[PDB]
View (cartoon, one colour):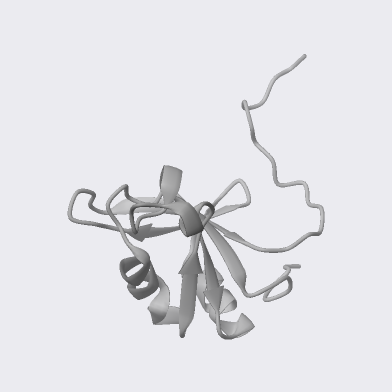
Length: 114
């Protein structure tokens, strides 16, 4: 059993290079269908890059989020893809399709017996 395309056309991405812009983040995910890319504080920024290495993809179709899910790697319920820049190469990046339902996928601080 799986959630598939359910949620929204928004997808969070973490681990992005410090030197990648909107059109390179777009070209990195355009393989799934047309989209636009946005991030916090962009309205007040002096630079065209995502702050702290994270952004939100907005696809034209929910099928493009499922196409991304079908290309992602997996660990502990986290999903991963890969990207690059003039300064960073072969970088893995964490993928989080937007959905408000609860789930048991959590691994923070690791396992412990007591």
